[PDB]
Image: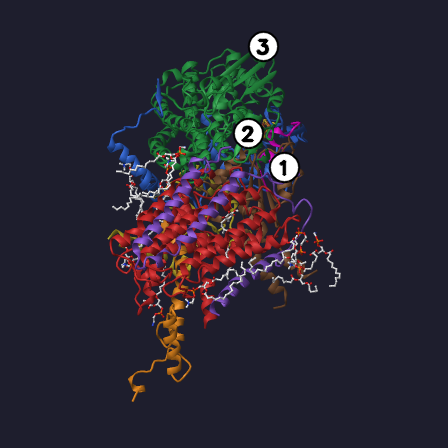
């Protein structure tokens, strides 16, 4: 056949085309492989936290949450209730950040450019929530083993309410442009069909499973933090194609607003990190007056806290699918091994199967529907 | 005085094309909640001039293994034909008053497909030859419906003279009797000019390069002028064809103002559509032409051949 | 007149043209591409400075290297740079492209894209805010406004 | 005359812009430049594009359809005849055979793009 | 609890079939998409007039680094090297020795602003609020060497941004 | 705001208006203030050539009326 | 009547900048002719304006000085010319000038 080299995240496709049809798709990854998993072995558990902001750099605080849940599990400590509600609050804001990127850059790739600009004026307002809690628009490093770094600034919850009060209308404007559009439907309907059994055997997760009717979501089957105290519905597809997965992501954005409306009303008072100075650093006003607090501030920031020896696989329902870390501890301050299970790694491996009997222009649609970011695929 | 007339046509066209790039970036800007160029000159008015100077003082890269003769011929053919199609247009008085003006427009339009073909050949790339073949197949497919649609409308006008379409619409726009034909004509002029949602080559950026991806600097600018000169001309053709303006021989400037407004709005409709829709897959825009547009165009050609005869409304030959 | 006057004004004309029509080809490699997409978003709207959202390599004036540059990707970044018509400028965005960043000591990372291509402006941050990147582009316009290509040619 | 001057002016202006588009700018050429763009990676084969049969059939289908349009062009002048019944029958016969030609390719999978 | 996104049976009465035929032939739902972009053309754009207008930030913003002083002018840093231990990117290099008056002070304090990930761990670790990340984010350079800060550059930033760094710390230290 | 797009549109509109006005006013300047004769068919050309021989001067747009007949 | 009040606001921006020269000056230096309330002026010549009816992000702006530290800044304005005391207010890190 004809062998082409498409590409310049950055990807390289070695495709074999019989005219307009795709005969085999051979993704070449590692263009953004950086040795994150090897570098983490030279860092303390706190120093390794910013590495997870940079794996899936559209869902920063969900990557932080998964790592914190893993370290908290090996530590055998529990974050306080207010911190958990904050993590769910910003986990769902992070879901909106990712789904806007997934839906709108997917639409941009297939020629629909306008919705990208509308919804990136809402991302620019959600980046202000990130910046007001952590000081960084994207790589907050706000979620940490033990809870969150700082408490919410006064007035932030009023601004989260004003934003969420108008976001439903913005999703409707998006749907008015895509959902019933015949050109958009022709590019997504019956494209990249995945059967339920193939989806499971190929290791898919997230909307890839749910687009094909599989009723699975870790926020409901294996809840973490306070997701079992929030009411929301899990969208389920029927055809298993790109269009059904597109609707699942758009409906999930509406359910995040539903959850966010509850984290604002049910936010409890209290502290925002575990009241255990051998894990979480003391307050600065007590590190400067108490001898115990100064010793623990000194040790937590130089040596770090020791994690009991053990190995855990901890996973969360990240916006892109099941995100998990297999974290191995040897009893010291530094992880012995940290395998990062990126949901897009298994999805991309299934591009060759999902692209059988499709045109070259459907590969763009298929890659968009898998919601692939090569920071987490390559690591 | 005739050589003055030619320049009074060519130069304003190249200025209209220049400031269509500004309007496209500002109409798309505001439809996307932003402003577009407003820094280079007041309200961006100097932006086309900066882009023009920039392009013509940049390296005009030509790959060493490219056929030089065809690499140079293609932009000359494209722009030369782009300006040629403007000479018979009755705005309200043609520069060259042709008896077969409509057929001249079709004849020159079908020659412009060569520039796409020659440019693809000259690249010696094969990342652009496939693009050229895809682009050429699209263009020739959609000039089948342009000819048959245009033939159907001329059966209510009587002749191929472009000025006779003014007389035909002296009582009513041809869009009412022929709105089914006008709809497909508008889409067919979008696909001929490779405008969204039919831009599989120019800016698809979906594992498909454009036939002029290898052009840079001035030669790229010339292709751009030809492409944008055709967008205005096709929309001016649509205004004359379906939105005829009344012509007062004593105040001909009244026609030009009204006809200029309609052409601008139709041109701004091209910009409106690019901001609103995704793009057809290549095999879908062929099915649009061969399976949807062509069957309907043929039926409406049969209907418009027999409608004048059965209503005793055959137009005069002169 | 003096000759130097005509050349001085012609420099301003071509300097003004080149900085008012900067067409960037963005190498979105890692997270820093997201902050580059927020500069194209409505709030900052780089298109209003004459800076188009995206351009193909053959019509691009500046290359924005936005993200970690790995050894595997290094040959491909040089190839795209070599094929950019001149004048060509390179903006290094973020720590990873600037000097290696978080992954400086990695076995698979180019410790700064200035090892592969010349760089005209370095934008610091991890990531730089969309406004800090727009400050770099505006800082590249002033650099081009200081060029004296013709004044130097006139004195050869 | 007026037409020849117009064509000469249009195509001379295009040629002038091309020459000043190749001589005005400052050039600098080297082997890494002046190579096909590809996508940043080296070519994967020294062979030309494979021949695709489907792209050949659209060109032929356009040609045969374009030839039948040539016969339909004189219809506006044909409607002025005194033998309208004969003219109308032959006008509809030509268009119907054009549709029958379309129906044949459609049902024989001639308009598809799936290999 | 789950919900179906695309599980519907279109009605097959002539009223509904003719509605879908009208949509297919009259392009009704495509023109509805043109009305959504027409509305935006008549809204106020969200663009700001940078550099004359600036995007909003908070007191917690992490920008360019700076070394601070006490009100007397003595350097706050006492060369404890906590910021150097916690720095996840190893961007801080410190050398110290007793000063002529016997105090514990640095002789080298370099931040490689090209290794730094602007994470803020250095100002969290610091026990005397010496090293901070200021509010400046507009310090792009023309060379790689201008971004290898030494102690003189960092002390110049502190004396340059103290008026604004002090105010930001005053507005956020109760959350720390 | 949206009306800041009009200055670019007005410049484009004026450019599209010049070709139509110039042709209209050049023809009248070159044809004695009237519309340029349209000769699509030989009969229309025959009369125009006849008007060129009847004007005394070699110009088909100079009209001779009843004052030229006695 | 409302459309007639639009042209009046557009005419009082010319008078609000001190005639046609002041109007054209800010139009070509700042690409914007809005009139705000003068909040203050710094020792380098920058003038700071506010207009609280504008949407958040455009309700504060600075018209840069035409000369600073010996550099002609009439055309070459830069965001780093804002001193720290006004850098906090102009970026909305505080409500107190
Ligand atoms: C020598 C020199 O001075 O440079 C000559 C110049 C470039 O040749 P070159 O400098 O030797 O560079 C070739 C490479 O070095 C050699 O390598 P290369 O691969 O880059 O060049 C290969 C090229 C070589 O082409 C040539 O060199 C021919 C000269 O191959 C050919 O085209 C063969 C020449 C036959 C051309 C057709 C006659 O040739 C041109 O391209 C200019 C002439 C072609 C443009 C003519 C435009 C005028 C007509 C347009 C107005 C009328 C409208 C017509 C509409 C179309 C109707 C058909
Ligand atoms: C490949 O990327 C890009 C595209 O492709 C998707 C584009 O369309 C565009 C679109 C925008 C442009 C401004 C490009 C064309 C610029 C011009 C200035 C057109 C040429 C203008 C002239 C006035 C020609 C000179 C003739 C004159 C003055 C007559 C006398 C850009 C910028 C781009 O970068
Ligand atoms: C130079 C590059 C040429 C580019 C090719 C396209 C040029 C246009 C072709 C001529 C247009 C035409 O058909 O005339 C229709 C029109 C038909 O208009 P008409 O039928 O209404 O006649 C006008 C006058 N009445 C009605 C009274 C009879 O021709 C004319 O208007 C006048 C004919 C003059 C012929 C002089 C030109 C002859 C040479 C033309 C070919 C040029 C060489 C081609 C080179 C190879 C090109 C690939
Ligand atoms: C139908 C009502 C149209 C207005 C009208 O009444 O005009 C009458 C008048 C009619 O004038 P007239 O010169 O055509 O004379 C009419 C009489 N007959 C039919 C005999 C010629 O229009 C004008 O005078 C000025 C033209 C303005 C209206 C043109 C509308 C065409 C718009 C088509 C494109 C639409 C896309 C818009 C995109 C905007 C968003 C970017
Ligand atoms: C008694 C008198 C009898 C006289 C005859 C009566 C005629 C009755 C009416 C005839 C039917 C109407 C035909 C309308 C044209 C058919 C279009 C068509 O084929 O649709 C199907 C096609 C295909 O639809 P599909 O994708 O759903 O597929 C249909 C067929 N299947 C499902 C089997 C595959 O749709 C399109 O045309 C796509 C449109 C894309 C264009 C996007 C831009 C639109 C923006 C609006 C522009 C408005 C233009 C206005 C221009 C004005 C200029 C002056
Ligand atoms: C050969 C015989 C000597 C003739 C003089 C000569 O060769 O050099 C003239 C030179 C040689 O060309 P050149 O190759 O040195 O030009 C390269 C690019 N510039 C102009 C920036 C130096 O011709 C010129 O370029 C002079 C300017 C005319 C071209 C640009 C404007 C009109 C198009
Ligand atoms: C200054 C600018 C002035 C306004 C310029 C005109 C703007 C027109 C575009 C905006 C339309 C508003 C949106 C809207 O109402 O659409 C909803 C409506 C309904 O959209 P719908 O598809 O959602 O309706 C579904 C329900 N059924 C099936 C029952 C209709 O759109 C229409 O009704 C348009 C029908 C007419 C289109 C005819 C085809 C075009 C032919 C052109 C001539 C040839
Ligand atoms: C009240 C009465 C109202 C009028 C009643 C008319 C009823 C007859 C018309 C409807 C019958 C249509 C037949 C049909 O359904 O064809 C379907 C089939 C579609 O095939 P296909 O799209 O490839 O399959 C799906 C692939 N995804 O189609 C095919 O496979 C082939 C279809 C070929 C059609 C070619 C037509 C082109 C010419 C247009 C008609 C011109 C007039 C013909 C002459 C008529 C003279 C009277
Ligand atoms: C028609 C146009 C003819 C002019 C062609 C000039 C040659 C092409 C050119 O411009 O290159 C000039 C060349 C140096 O430039 P180049 O080698 O192309 O690449 C430099 C990249 N840094 O400079 C060179 O070194 C070679 C320049 C050509 C030498 C010509 C010698 C003339 C010999 C007599 C010719 C017969 C009399 C006429
Ligand atoms: C702000 C909202 C508008 C936004 C822009 C939208 C419109 C774009 C422009 C549309 C096209 C119109 C262009 C403007 C041209 C108007 C000029 C004019 O008023 O007419 C000039 C005309 C002079 O021509 P002339 O033939 O000499 O007049 C006869 C004298 N014996 O004098 C006349 O006789 C005319 C009668
Ligand atoms: S500099 Fe920071 S934001 Fe940019 S690619 Fe590197 S880690 Fe990501
Ligand atoms: S911000 Fe983080 S990476 Fe930068 S110097 Fe401080 S601790 Fe190191
Ligand atoms: S800056 Fe602070 S943490 Fe770093 S050495 Fe000085 S006192 Fe210690």
Q: Which mark is residue A23?
A: 2
Chain that is green in the image: A
Which residue is found at the position 68% from the left and 31% from the top?
A: E100
Establish whether ligand 12 lies closer than 8 Å to the Cβ of label 3: no
Q: Which of marks 3 and 2 precedes in the sequence?
A: 2
Q: Disc 2 to disc 3, how far (Cα)?
A: 48 Å
Is disc 1 surrounded by few (<14), some (14 to 19) or many (20+) residues within 10 Å? Answer: some
Structure colour scheme:
by chain
Instruction: In this rendered view, identify the residue nearer to me: A238 or A134.
Output: A238
Which residue is tagged 1?
Answer: D41
Picture quadrant of residue A24: top right
Q: Which residue bears the numbered disc 3?
A: A309
Chain letter for red, please: B
Q: Chain C appears in which tint?
A: brown
Which chain hosts label 2? A
Q: Which chain is yellow?
A: G
Check the rendered structure and report the hue given to chain D: purple
Write down the region rendered in magenta: C91-108
Compared across the picture, whether B41 is left or right of A11 comes to left
The residue lying at 42 percent from left, 15 percent from top is A223
């Amino acid at each position: 056949n004809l062998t082409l080299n498409f590409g310049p995240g950055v990807l390289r496709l070695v495709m074999e085309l019989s005219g307009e049809m795709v005969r085999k798709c051979d993704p070449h990854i590692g263009l953004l492989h950086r040795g994150t998993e090897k570098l983490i072995e030279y860092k303390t558990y706190l120093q390794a936290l910013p590495y997870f902001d940079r794996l899936d750099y559209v869902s920063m605080m969900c990557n932080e949450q998964a790592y914190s849940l893993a370290v908290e599990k090996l530590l055998n400590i529990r974050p306080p209730p207010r911190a958990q509600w904050i993590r769910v609050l910003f986990g769902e804001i992070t879901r909106l950040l990712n789904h806007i990127m997934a839906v709108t850059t997917h639409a941009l790739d297939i020629g629909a450019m306008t919705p990208f600009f509308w919804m990136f004026e809402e991302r620019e307002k959600m980046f202000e929530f990130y910046e007001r809690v952590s000081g960084a628009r994207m790589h907050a490093a706000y979620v940490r083993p033990g809870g969150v770094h700082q408490d919410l600034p006064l007035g932030l919850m009023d601004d989260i309410y004003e934003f969420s009060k108008n976001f439903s209308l913005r999703i409707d404007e998006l749907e008015e442009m895509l959902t019933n559009n015949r050109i958009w439907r022709n590019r997504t309907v019956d494209i990249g069909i995945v059967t339920a059994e193939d989806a499971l055997n190929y290791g898919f997760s997230g909307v890839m499973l749910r687009g094909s009717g599989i009723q699975w979501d870790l926020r409901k089957t294996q809840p973490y933090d306070v997701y079992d105290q929030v009411e929301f519905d899990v969208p389920i597809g029927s055809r298993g194609d790109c269009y059904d997965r597109y609707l699942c992501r758009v409906e999930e954005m509406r359910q995040s607003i539903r959850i966010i409306s509850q984290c604002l009303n049910k936010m409890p008072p209290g502290e925002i990190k575990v009241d255990d100075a051998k894990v979480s650093p003391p307050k600065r006003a007590e590190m400067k007056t108490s001898m115990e607090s100064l010793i623990h501030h000194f040790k937590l920031y130089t040596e770090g806290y020791q994690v009991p020896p053990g190995a855990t696989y901890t996973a969360i329902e990240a916006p892109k699918g099941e995100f998990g870390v297999y974290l191995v501890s040897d009893g010291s301050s530094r992880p012995y091994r940290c395998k990062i299970k990126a949901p897009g790694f298994a999805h991309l491996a299934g591009l060759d199967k999902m692209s059988k009997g499709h045109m070259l222009a459907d590969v763009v649609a298929i890659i968009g529907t898998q919601d692939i970011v090569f920071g987490e695929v390559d690591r | 005085m005739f050589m003055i007339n030619i320049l009074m046509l060519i130069i304003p066209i190249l200025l209209a094309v220049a400031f269509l790039t500004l309007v496209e970036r500002k109409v798309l800007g505001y439809m996307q909640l932003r402003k577009g160029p407003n820094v280079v000159g007041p309200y961006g008015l100097l932006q086309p001039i900066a882009d023009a100077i920039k392009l013509f003082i940049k390296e005009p890269l030509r790959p060493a293994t490219s056929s030089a003769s065809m690499f140079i011929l293609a932009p000359i053919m494209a722009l030369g034909l782009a300006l040629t199609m403007w000479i018979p247009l009755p705005m309200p008085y043609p520069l060259i008053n042709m008896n077969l003006g409509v057929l001249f427009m079709l004849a020159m339009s079908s020659l412009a497909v060569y520039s796409i073909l020659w440019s693809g050949w000259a690249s010696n790339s094969k990342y652009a030859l496939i693009g050229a073949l895809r682009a050429v197949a699209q263009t020739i497919s959609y000039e089948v419906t342009l000819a048959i649609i245009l033939l159907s409308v001329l059966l209510m006008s009587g002749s191929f003279t472009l000025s006779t379409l003014i007389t035909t619409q002296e009582q009513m726009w041809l869009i009412l009797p022929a709105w089914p034909l006008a709809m497909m004509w508008f889409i067919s002029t979008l696909a001929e000019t490779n405008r969204a949602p039919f831009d599989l080559t120019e800016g698809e950026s979906e594992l498909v390069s454009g036939f002029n991806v290898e052009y840079a600097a001035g030669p790229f600018a010339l292709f751009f002028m030809a492409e944008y000169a055709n967008i205005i001309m096709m929309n001016i053709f649509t205004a004359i064809l379906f939105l005829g303006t009344s012509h007062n021989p004593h105040m001909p400037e009244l026609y030009t103002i009204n006809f200029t407004i309609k052409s601008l709005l139709l041109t701004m409709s091209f910009l409106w559509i690019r901001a609103s829709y995704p793009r057809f897959r290549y095999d879908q825009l062929m099915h649009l032409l061969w399976k949807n547009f062509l069957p309907l165009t043929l039926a409406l050609c049969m209907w418009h051949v027999s409608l004048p005869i059965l209503t005793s409304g055959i137009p005069p030959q002169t | 007149s003096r000759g130097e006057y005509v050349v001085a004004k012609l420099d301003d004309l071509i300097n003004w043209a080149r900085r008012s029509s900067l067409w960037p080809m963005t190498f979105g490699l890692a997270c820093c591409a997201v902050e580059m997409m927020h500069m194209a978003a409505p709030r900052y709207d780089m298109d209003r400075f004459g800076v188009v959202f995206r351009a193909s390599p053959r019509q691009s004036d500046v290359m924005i290297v936005a993200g970690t540059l790995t050894n595997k990707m290094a040959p491909a970044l040089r190839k795209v740079y070599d094929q950019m018509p001149e004048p060509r400028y390179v903006v290094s965005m973020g720590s990873c492209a600037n000097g290696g960043g978080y992954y400086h000591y990695s076995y698979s990372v180019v410790r700064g894209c200035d090892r592969i291509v010349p760089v005209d402006i370095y934008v610091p941050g991890c990531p730089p805010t969309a406004e800090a990147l727009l400050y770099g582009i505006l800082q590249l316009q002033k650099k081009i406004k200081r060029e004296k290509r013709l004044r130097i040619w006139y004195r050869r | 005359m007026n037409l020849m001057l117009a064509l000469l002016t249009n195509f001379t202006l295009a040629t002038l812009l091309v020459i000043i588009a190749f001589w005005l700018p400052q050039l600098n050429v080297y082997s890494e430049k002046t190579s096909p763009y590809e996508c940043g990676f080296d070519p994967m084969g020294s062979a030309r594009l494979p021949f695709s049969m489907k792209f050949f059939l659209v060109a032929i289908t356009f040609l045969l359809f374009d030839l039948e349009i040539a016969l339909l062009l004189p219809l506006p002048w044909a409607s002025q005849t005194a033998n309208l019944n004969t003219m109308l029958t032959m006008a509809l016969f030509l268009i119907i055979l054009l549709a029958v030609s379309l129906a044949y390719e459609w049902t024989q999978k001639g308009l598809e793009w799936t290999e | 609890t789950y919900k179906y996104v695309n599980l519907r049976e279109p009605s097959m009465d002539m009223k509904s079939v003719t509605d879908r035929a009208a949509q297919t032939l009259l392009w009704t739902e495509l023109i509805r998409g043109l009305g959504m972009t027409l509305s935006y053309l008549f809204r106020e754009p969200a663009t700001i007039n940078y550099p004359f207008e600036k995007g909003p930030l908070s007191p917690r913003f992490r920008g360019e680094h700076a070394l601070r002083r006490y009100p007397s002018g003595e350097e706050r840093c006492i060369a404890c090297k906590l910021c150097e231990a916690v720095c996840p990117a190893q961007a801080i290099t410190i050398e110290a020795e007793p000063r002529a008056d016997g105090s514990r002070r640095t002789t080298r304090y370099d931040i490689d602003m090209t290794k730094c990930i602007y994470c803020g761990f250095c100002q969290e670790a610091c026990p005397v609020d010496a090293i901070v990340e200021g509010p400046n984010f507009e310090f792009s350079t023309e060379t790689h060497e201008e971004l290898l800060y030494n102690k003189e550059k960092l002390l110049n930033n502190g004396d340059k941004w103290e008026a604004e760094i002090a105010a930001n710390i005053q507005a956020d230290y109760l959350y720390r | 705001m949206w009306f800041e797009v009009l200055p670019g549109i007005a410049v484009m509109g004026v450019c599209l208006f010049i070709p139509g006005m110039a042709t209209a006013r050049i023809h009248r300047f070159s044809n004695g203030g009237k519309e340029k004769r349209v000769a699509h068919y030989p009969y229309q050309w025959y009369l125009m050539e006849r008007d060129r021989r009847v004007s005394g001067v070699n110009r088909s747009y100079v009209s001779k009326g009843l004052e030229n007949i006695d | 009547m409302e459309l007639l009040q639009v042209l009046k606001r557009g005419l009082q921006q010319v008078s609000g900048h001190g005639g046609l020269r002041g109007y054209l000056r800010v139009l070509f230096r700042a690409n914007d002719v809005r009139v705000g309330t003068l909040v203050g002026e710094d020792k380098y010549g920058n003038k700071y304006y506010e207009d609280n009816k504008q949407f958040f992000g455009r309700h504060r702006w600075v018209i840069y000085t035409t000369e600073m530290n010996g550099k002609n800044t009439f055309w070459d304005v830069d965001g780093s010319m804002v001193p720290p005391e006004w850098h906090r207010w102009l970026h909305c890190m505080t409500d107190d000038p």
